[PDB]
Image: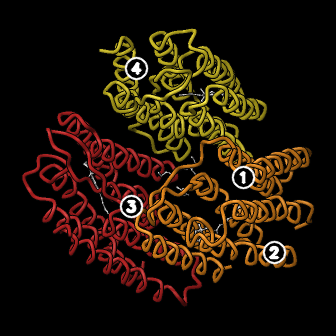
Chain colours: A yellow, B red, C orange
Amino acid sequence: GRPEWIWLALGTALMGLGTLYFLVKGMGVSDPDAKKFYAITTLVPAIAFTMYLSMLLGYGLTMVPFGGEQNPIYWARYADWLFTTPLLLLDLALLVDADQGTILALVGADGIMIGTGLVGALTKVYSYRFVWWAISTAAMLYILYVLVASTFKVLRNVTVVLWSAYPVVWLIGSEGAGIVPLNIETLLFMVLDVSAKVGFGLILLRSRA
Amino acid sequence: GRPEWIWLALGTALMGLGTLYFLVKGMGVSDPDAKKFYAITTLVPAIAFTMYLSMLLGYGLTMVPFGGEQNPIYWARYADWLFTTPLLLLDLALLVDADQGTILALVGADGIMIGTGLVGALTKVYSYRFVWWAISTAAMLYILYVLVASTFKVLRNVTVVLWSAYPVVWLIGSEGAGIVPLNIETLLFMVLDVSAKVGFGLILLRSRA
Amino acid sequence: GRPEWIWLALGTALMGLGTLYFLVKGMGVSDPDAKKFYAITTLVPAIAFTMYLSMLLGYGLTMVPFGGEQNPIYWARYADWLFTTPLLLLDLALLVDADQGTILALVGADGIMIGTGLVGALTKVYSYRFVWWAISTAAMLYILYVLVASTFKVLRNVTVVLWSAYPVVWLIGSEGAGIVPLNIETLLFMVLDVSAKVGFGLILLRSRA
Ligand SMILES: *C/C=C(C)/C=C/C=C(C)/C=C/C1=C(C)CCCC1(C)C
Ligand SMILES: *C/C=C(C)/C=C/C=C(C)/C=C/C1=C(C)CCCC1(C)C
Ligand SMILES: *C/C=C(C)/C=C/C=C(C)/C=C/C1=C(C)CCCC1(C)C
Ligand SMILES: CCCCCCC
Ligand SMILES: CCCCCCC
Ligand SMILES: CCCCCCC
């Protein structure tokens, strides 16, 4: 129906598969610590799965009026990111044994980041979308700024790299400037999401930290 | 007005009453541990009270189009369950001193469970409602799978038993197949809710664990 | 456009400024404890900033039908208060080293307080708005009831005093009786909000507790 359906069906399948893989691997885990990393890392694609599926079916899609057009906005991504991004930071934070003080900074900057992104997404005055983008981007840079040694270091690098593309994709995509069509937009986010969650989780869960 | 009002007024009264009872009983509690069980167990009907009331008044009711009809859906139940179900699992988890790792699995599976139930409830393609039902049901079975010795054992049994009816009621009720009318549906959930919260709480709070 | 814009622009600027001040001051903080108070206290105006801005721009404003009129309701305040009020109680609670049991009572009573306030705000039957007001007010009195020695004592007093005006303002404002216009209403909340967050935070962060 919608040309981007194939990328949504595919992300659904890969988050679906990735969840099951992590579930099965986390069986045989007595370790308090590993228990924690496993619950976190399996929850991330499990949530992604549900929101890829809601997008695949018409549910996590709405039409937002701006620039003289009704524009198709996938709101379900923010509902995913709202929980999946703090869990990933929490994976990193527990890894290096961050202070409560620092987790709350990361987690709270993270909610502001995707909170303001959602507002950007649904804002009906074109110009103001970019104000909300700018604010969310500044909350992202705070997180990067704030962001065993070896796998943390690797995981942080992957994070810094993949997370940074998201505002770039949103900015040039249908949420922002409309220069890259929803189609390739949805592919781009698909590859990003699977790498930041299943990829990130493979790295983390097969590692000894 | 609506034939099911009497069951909503009644659940409101019983959650209202149950909250006050637990409040009054929790006075004279110096114990850190008991403090924790009391705050949890009193919060559960206090939230239920507000959502029984929002349903009683027209607020937590919307009309969802599917199957060629506009169908009356009580969305306020999910807003209740979203917080009340993790608190009940938390009562059980603290009881047996579960790992952080395991609480996060329970709590996160619980949010997916009622998260997907809400989507099921509001989904406008009849067939897809049942996909969302199936996913939520599978998250429920995970929780049951994951789920002093004596009161835990009793409390777990009550939980396993009453929680399992909910998807059955939803499936045959107005959310699903429309074979049991909203009326008796609302009665059924009423009895279930009061038993899983006030009943569960009586058992737990009068016990010595 | 809207006469109350000047108070929204102003609250935006002061929450904006207050956030930056606290950020800059929290640099050079190695202390686990102070780390915690700083993350909490900086998050509070950072969130307020975003919701003052959403209100300034048309976003956090909706029209609710009651009393034969469509009434302008600023829903974005509840989205602010939902997170900012538990963080402030958490500042107080950590200050005096409250039990987990007591934090959960405070935090959960706090969510019910602003939860029911939101319902009040959007309720389309005039009379019922005041039922929801009454319930939220009773959850507030519970919190006050439940609510180093010196700065706690000072901070508690400020809290008791400023928080208590909010239901008074809502009751006489456009949410309730419509006796005080939105204009002065927005000014009143503006002064209250800046005092309860930036004022409260100055007191707390310059203090040695
Ligand atoms: C699994 C999903 C991941 C790791 C997604 C991360 C998303 C972000 C870092 C999003 C950032 C955004 C901005 C900085 C502004 C524009 C809107 C967003 C939400 C795309
Ligand atoms: C106090 C309320 C309780 C304990 C409610 C528990 C509710 C559930 C276990 C609901 C489960 C559902 C499914 C498994 C799928 C269909 C939708 C739900 C949300 C009714
Ligand atoms: C920074 C913001 C603060 C401290 C706001 C606090 C708000 C309240 C204590 C609000 C209380 C309300 C009622 C008790 C009933 C009417 C609705 C509210 C939400 C204004
Ligand atoms: C949106 C993620 C924050 C939820 C935390 C409430 C304690
Ligand atoms: C919906 C229950 C989860 C809220 C947790 C955020 C930390
Ligand atoms: C609304 C504040 C509560 C979020 C807590 C979920 C654990």
Q: Secondary structure at mark 4?
A: helix
Q: Please state which of the two labelled residues, at mark 4 or mark 3, is closer to the viewer.
A: 3
In the displayed structure, would residue C78 be above or below residue B33?
Answer: above
In the displayed structure, would residue A189 be above or below residue B33?
Answer: above
Ligand 6 quadrant in view:
bottom right
Q: Which mark is residue A11?
A: 4
Q: Amino acid at mark 3?
A: Asp
Is label 3 on the same chain as label 1? no
Percent coordinates x, y for residue A126 in the rendering: 61, 25
Percent coordinates x, y for residue A197 in the rendering: 51, 26
Residue that carries the numbered disc 2 in the rendered image: C152
Q: CA distance from mark 4 to mark 2?
A: 50 Å
Pointer 3 indicates a residue of which chain?
B
Q: Amino acid at mark 2?
A: Phe
Percent coordinates x, y for residue B161 in the rendering: 21, 62
Instruction: Classify mark 1: residues with Cα within 10 Å, few (<14), some (14-19) or many (20+).
Output: few
Q: How many marks?
A: 4
What residue is rendered at 72% in x and 28% in y? A134
Question: Horizontally, is C102 left or right of B116 in the view?
Answer: right
Q: Please state which of the two labelled residues, at mark 1 or mark 2, is closer to the viewer.
A: 1
Q: CA distance from mark 1 to mark 2?
A: 38 Å
**Disc 3 C-beta below 8 A from ligand 2:** yes
Q: Secondary structure at mark 3?
A: helix
Q: CA distance from mark 2 to mark 3?
A: 34 Å
Q: Are marks 4 and 3 in contact (CB under 8 Å)?
A: no
Q: Secondary structure at mark 2?
A: helix
User: Where, quadrant-wise, is the N terminus of chain A in this rendering?
Assistant: top left
Residue that carries the numbered disc 3 in the rendered image: B80
Question: Horizontally, is B94 left or right of C60 in the view?
Answer: left
Residue that carries the numbered disc 1 in the rendered image: C3
Q: CA distance from mark 1 to mark 4?
A: 48 Å
Question: Horizontally, is A92 left or right of A54 in the view?
Answer: right
